[PDB]
Image (cartoon, coloured by chain):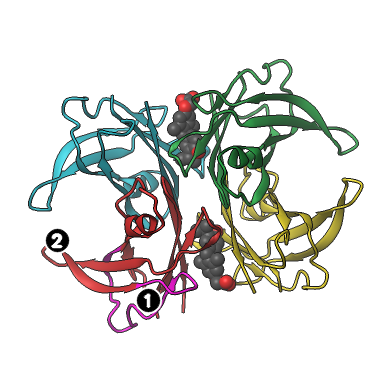
Chain colours: A red, B cyan, C green, D yellow
Amino acid sequence: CPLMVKVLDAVRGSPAINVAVHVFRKAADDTWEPFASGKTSESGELHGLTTEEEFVEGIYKVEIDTKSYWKALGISPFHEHAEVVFTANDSGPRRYTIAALLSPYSYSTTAVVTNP
Amino acid sequence: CPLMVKVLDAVRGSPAINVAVHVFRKAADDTWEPFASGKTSESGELHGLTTEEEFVEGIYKVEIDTKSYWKALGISPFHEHAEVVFTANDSGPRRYTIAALLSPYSYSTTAVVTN
Amino acid sequence: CPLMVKVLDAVRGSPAINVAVHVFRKAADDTWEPFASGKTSESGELHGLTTEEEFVEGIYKVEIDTKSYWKALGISPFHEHAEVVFTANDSGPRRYTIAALLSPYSYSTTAVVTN
Amino acid sequence: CPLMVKVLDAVRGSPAINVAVHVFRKAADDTWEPFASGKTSESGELHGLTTEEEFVEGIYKVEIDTKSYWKALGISPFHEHAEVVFTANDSGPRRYTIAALLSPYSYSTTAVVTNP
Ligand SMILES: Cc1cc(OCC(=O)O)cc(C)c1Cc1ccc(O)c(C(C)C)c1
Ligand SMILES: Cc1cc(OCC(=O)O)cc(C)c1Cc1ccc(O)c(C(C)C)c1
């Protein structure tokens, strides 16, 4: 898969399990069209969101439901979600790993972009 | 002010200067209504976005134009911007500092919520 | 001062208060000589560690006692501390702010080097 | 292996390749004894540092040579290295992944600790 999401929990030092992830792609009319969705596994990973054929050039948004994650652990976090927005495939097809590191009042996100 | 934004540049080890920042409030129809904006100062700070009277409870989005910043420095960036979405809440402390740390392919953001 | 330390808590969304910080300078024999120390303020800041005269070029280590901080909050931490090791250099800007962002199993540190 | 190190470059959005890593363990006399060393692979990973038998309880230091990494890319970075110090195995054997994210003037580090 050309798009993978990996989420870690900085409080527990663990993968962030069962985190909902929604992906959108900006349409020609500038709206966000639903593209794919899933939830992270026991390893904090979400694979199989898309395919090489489908994942064309465009502006994509990956919205990670961090608030539901923290709420289920009894925590009222600051952010509603973590949303990473990016242009994909503009110099040709690439593989993207979107890595997120979560704390109740902070998150970081990083992209690892490789040429397949 | 109840809301301040502070932006640092992890490549240069400096405040991130002249970064455009837009603030939006979520409307009843779930659209984002522009609320305030500015550019960060020589110290990477943006003050005076709102007032205590105006900044009522709601869902807010702070959009930091990281892409234009990296473009101005001749460095290829990954993100279109960094968005920071949160519910502002009266019961808690209520001065918010949104701190962001920028790299071309990574950012972190943290909230410092006080008094 | 030429050196300031600012520490934030990513769990509480607050300055990290009363965190012990020790500064060391690398000696000629490669050992670390204690130089200065303090505890962060109510704003998570530690000022006045050194002076422009004293803070000559050399290799410095700032050790932030994160473990005692998490212990004080009843939260299990991973690291013994966060160390920040750098060469201080006259040609460049020379006011250093060491910013640290703390979580129980993660920390980040950044240098803001100005004027 | 109970200890793995993974290093990413936040400027290029890539693994950080050929980064030297030195591991030390605190001795009974409070000195740092050399424990293991290696360098990151093309995937930014360093495997095989130790074994279950060898990796007993103790205080360990993982020193990642970030300065040489940046210097080889023409950059004069702020830090001499990234050094992550931690007590290991104090509630029994665990697997540790030490993840580091590098920028010229900043780094973050995170531990993922799992029960084998
Ligand atoms: C929020 C903030 C306040 C501050 O006050 C000290 C000053 O203005 O001199 C000084 C600095 C440098 C920051 C920014 C900061 C301070 C600490 C920190 O962990 C982070 C994370 C985003 C990496 C950011
Ligand atoms: C992206 C990624 C890939 C990975 O490969 C799987 C494995 O080898 O276990 C293993 C891990 C732990 C990560 C996550 C990671 C790896 C490095 C890193 O600096 C960061 C920051 C976002 C904190 C995250």
State the residue position of label 1.
A93
Q: Residue at x 30, y 45 (%)?
A: B65
Amino acid type of the residue that numbered disc 1 sits on in the rendered structure: Pro
Chain designation of label 1: A
Q: Nearer the viewer, residue C24 or B68?
A: C24
Percent x, y of residue D10: 51, 55
Percent x, y of residue B21: 28, 39
Q: Main secondary structure of the magenta part?
A: loop
Q: Is A46 part of what is drawn in magenta?
A: yes
Q: Which mark is residue C99?
A: none
Percent x, y of residue D44: 61, 67
Occupied quadrant, residue D114: bottom right
Chain designation of label 2: A
Q: Is residue C2 left or right of residue B6?
A: right
**Up/down of B3 relative to D114, above or below:** above
Which of the two discs, 1 and 2, sits closer to the camera?
2
Amino acid type of the residue that numbered disc 2 sits on in the rendered structure: Asp
State the residue position of label 2.
A30
Q: Is residue C100 visible?
A: yes
Q: Nearer the viewer, residue D36 or A52?
A: D36
Occupied quadrant, residue B105: bottom left
SS for callout 1? loop
Q: Residues within 10 Å of mark 2 (few under 14, many from 20)?
A: few
Q: Residue at x 47, y 73 (%)?
A: A42
Q: CA distance from mark 1 to mark 2?
A: 22 Å
Q: Is residue D68 left or right of residue C30?
A: left
SS for callout 2? loop
Q: Is residue B105 visible?
A: no
**Residue bounds of the magenta highlight:** A39-62
